[PDB]
Length: 124
Length: 124
Length: 124
Length: 124
Image (cartoon, rainbow over all chains, first blue to last red; front, side, top):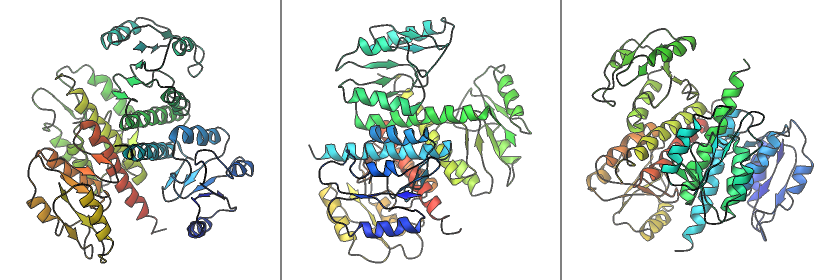
């Protein structure tokens, strides 16, 4: 029901993210800057505020969220025990079903081990 | 370097777990009761005490540990950022390498979604 | 609807496999010897004979079947395009749904990479 | 050592694919049209011709290859038993190691179940 988008410094690309979010059926808008820290939540804090039990979460791609699956799992799983579920759009995954949670944390597993192998490529 | 085993109330099965742990190369002994709670750590607390940076963790099977991957990932990943790594025996996985962490949290993903589908089978 | 069990040379363990298969709801019986080859099908050939479109497959564990996921995927996927589906019991997976096929070939992926790491442990 | 790229009808995008392939270290060039069939190999047939034992395979993304993991696994696994290995670039996976084959066929698993859920979205 509620959507959120992450980007660096340019805000023209989010306009066509926002478009597809609305079309996918959601109510409210949230967008953040990445200039500073991408694992310290800025205006995502307000997304946790305006969210209540039964409702859901809108995400284009898992990667555009935080990527660190240690930090990821230990957050979405807290909503799981707060009564609120989460779906990922072009990732194509829901947390609603136990069978469904699986694709999630293996895509979340992949998302980290993605960054973890990409970031070490920079060294040698 | 340090080993730990989980069981219900009988302690003859752990004797041949202990045997294979020693053979696999480890120093100290830790064993707990399951009578009460399996997600509230009893004498595992002492395993976190006698453990220091660089050292490792010995586990026969991931399942015999806690199973709840929300609770699992948010613990081993803390050692990952504490400088201490972890290997799983007959699960056949290490956390040492980033490529290696993968098999881990998809086996940990599996371990939860195992219990999650087993426990719901009891209902209807 | 139709069940199959794999074992080495002793046939007392299959009796309590057979029991749980029947209870899980299936019609016919199939059991093979492993003395010789485990990737060359013996009396499984008859299971492909007495099987028709719409019907399903009964398996206790994926491992007790062949394990080689190159050989596995390239067989079950043939039924997938023959109109016949497959479910795995204590593995807890169906091929019926596309979302469901996933847990399958990652458990099938695991089953191979299990044997592949177990068999290389024998060397050095 | 040898590279291959897949595209629809425009050939300007492959020019910057080709660029990164060369930089990643490979010898020869192969590119195909997608106008007709994407699961019936056209000028990929020549890639199987000019390839010998010990050598490797270059792929930008698994998806840009065929996607059908039934058809995928039952091909790469044939090289696996032909002595020739395969690496995937921005997918970041090799088949060289048994531990490595894993990320592969779960990314290959993902690639299919990607298309399988994308293609069914078109219906209703």
